[PDB]
Image: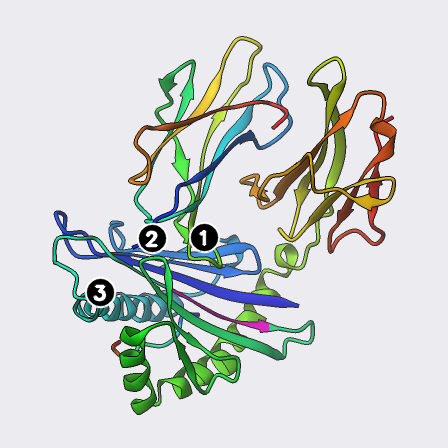
Amino acid sequence: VVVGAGGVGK
Amino acid sequence: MIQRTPKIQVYSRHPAENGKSNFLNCYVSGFHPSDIEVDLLKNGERIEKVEHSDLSFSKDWSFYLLYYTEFTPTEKDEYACRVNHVTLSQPKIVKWDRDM
Amino acid sequence: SHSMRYFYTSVSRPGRGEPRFIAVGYVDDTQFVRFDSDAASQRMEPRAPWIEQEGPEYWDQETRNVKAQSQTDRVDLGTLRGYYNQSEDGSHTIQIMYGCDVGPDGRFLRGYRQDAYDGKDYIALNEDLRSWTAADMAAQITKRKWEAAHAAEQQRAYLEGRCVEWLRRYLENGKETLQRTDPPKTHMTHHPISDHEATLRCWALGFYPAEITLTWQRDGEDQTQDTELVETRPAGDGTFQKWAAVVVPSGEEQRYTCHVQHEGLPKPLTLRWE
């Protein structure tokens, strides 16, 4: 499965 | 901004036997950026129904795709892969050699 | 031992539309999923037969999470264009690869997460999964935002957790195909290139996984001069192909041996021309 939604802007 | 020219191999899925159904492959790897045009040629004419694998990339971030079609090799027919890419001044042609 | 890997590409298209986003998922050297922002479905799609058995809840969640990532990458293309002082005229690429490795017992061995801009290293998660390496001063801005938001923690929780748990389930559902080690089928060809030289070509066909070594030896000593080694290539059926060639003095063919190493060969294989 893919890494969850809550990624952080660069 | 770095870019990389595509490497091209053109080859059959199985060892070529004349009159026996097979698949003609053109593997384009080692290139950047992702946008690329690939045609398979029979006697210098574009083969119409050509599929490709989904775009992926390698450890060095360079892209690779497989282009393929069903074909029946014969003694008289020549096949090639033609590639266009922003890194080339002219289309790069590789002729299918059945022992390569 | 086994790996799961995802491969994300976003490309800004000045003179076209929104960025093109493409995602592919792999277990070892087998692709199981894709997403393409230009395709009609707007869904994560199966690319292997053993993933087809996952229910619509799997496909809904996977589609939502990969679409969310495509949005982050769209905003990220704008931000990094700012950081490198580049015009709105040009096309730029963000790539991301991440994944986990498990041993033959299914236990966590390793996590990775790496990001590129325009084909070059931008930022990397370190092997401790707690800290980051930035390639340049633009990426140091990213690194400081990511330290302050504790982003390393969400990545570690994924790689030691869902990543490993779902790889185990993928290896069980696909056990019929993913546990296989298809050894190379080998042969050698010979072509006169002149009256005094000839080419020996050593072939490996129909092998899985992709990892293989072909080495030419002369009298037991490794030979690099007068060789060609092509890149391992897909057959398109789930197997891989490779060849290695050496130019030899004519009537000295018997001095050359080709050595084949592969996971699926119990004993290494040696080819010599008849």
The residue tagged with tag 1: helix, strand or loop? loop
Residue that mark 1 sits on: C47
Taken as a whole, is the magenta stretch helix, strand or loop?
strand
Task: Indicate which disc residue B2 carries.
Answer: 2
Q: CA distance from mark 2 to mark 1?
A: 31 Å
Task: Say what amino acid the circle numbered 2 marks.
Answer: Ile
Q: Give the quarter of the figure containing the C terminus of chain C.
A: top right
* Relative image position of residue C162 (x, y in whole percent): 48, 78
- The answer to whether residue A2 is seen in the rendering is yes
Q: Give the quarter of the figure containing the N terminus of chain C.
A: bottom right
In which chain is the residue bearing label 2? B
Q: How busy is the neighbourhood of tag 2: few (under 14 within 10 Å), some, or many (20 plus)?
A: few
Q: CA distance from mark 1 to mark 3?
A: 28 Å
The magenta stretch is: C96-101
Q: How busy is the neighbourhood of tag 3: few (under 14 within 10 Å), some, or many (20 plus)?
A: many
Task: Say what amino acid the circle numbered 1 marks.
Answer: Arg
* CB-based contact (under 8 Å), mark 1 and mark 3: no
Q: Residue at x 59, y 60 (%)?
A: C174
User: Do pointers 2 and 1 mark residues of a single chain?
Assistant: no
Is B60 located above or below residue C206 in the figure?
Answer: below
Residue that mark 3 sits on: C77
* Relative image position of residue B57 (x, y in whole percent): 43, 54
In reply to whether residue C99 is colored magenta, the answer given is: yes
* Relative image position of residue C96 (x, y in whole percent): 38, 65
* Relative image position of residue C48 (x, y in whole percent): 50, 53
Is B16 located above or below residue C159 in the figure?
Answer: above
Q: Residue at x 18, y 52 (%)?
A: C13
